[PDB]
Amino acid sequence: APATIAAGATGELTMYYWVPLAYSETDLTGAVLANVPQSKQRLKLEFAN
Amino acid sequence: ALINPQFPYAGPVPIPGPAPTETMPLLNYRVEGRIAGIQQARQFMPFLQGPHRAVAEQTYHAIGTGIQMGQTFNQPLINTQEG
């Protein structure tokens, strides 16, 4: 992300987030079995405005 | 089939089902069928039952007649050799 965006300028930003279910790549505590239901998962995201 | 715990596959389609109709009935058919037109014994065809000749043989009749008649000329007499 640009440190500053001057008057009249347009800045381009990139951000990444990891939403964990499993604790880590080797510890599956918290992981979700999703091949067991037709019932949908919901990942709700509210963005800046 | 796979079942996964803890999300288990419901143990049935349960009692909340919507019976939509009672139209289940096929009414038996009752009928009397008569196909009775007068039949006439015969049909016309161009040809039935023939085993037509692909080639015939040559065929003939016969005659002869006449008599035994003749005009003849003979060899001359000759000296006899031996005997």
Image (tube, coloured by chain):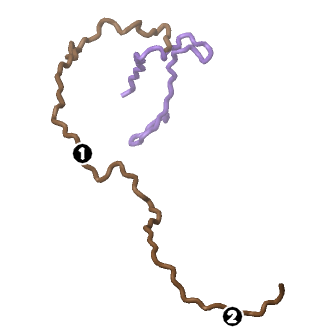
In the image, which lettered chain appears brown? B
Is B60 left, or right, of B31 in this rendering?
Answer: right
Circle 1 crowding by C-alpha within 10 Å: few under 14, some 14–19, many from 20: few
Of A27 and A37, the residue lying toward us: A37
Circle 2 crowding by C-alpha within 10 Å: few under 14, some 14–19, many from 20: few
Quadrant in the rendering for residue B42: top left
In the displayed structure, B65 sits above or below A25; it is below
Q: Amino acid at mark 1?
A: Gln
Is A16 left, or right, of B81 in this rendering?
Answer: left
In the image, which lettered chain appears purple? A
Is B32 left, or right, of B57 in this rendering?
Answer: left
Residue A36 at x, y percent in the picture: 47, 14
Q: Amino acid at mark 2?
A: Pro
Of B73 and B4, the residue lying toward us: B73
Q: Residue at x 39, y 40 (%)?
A: A7
In the displayed structure, B81 sits above or below B25; it is below
Query: Tags 1 and 2 in contact by the CB under 8 Å rule?
Result: no
Query: Mark 1 — residue?
Result: B43
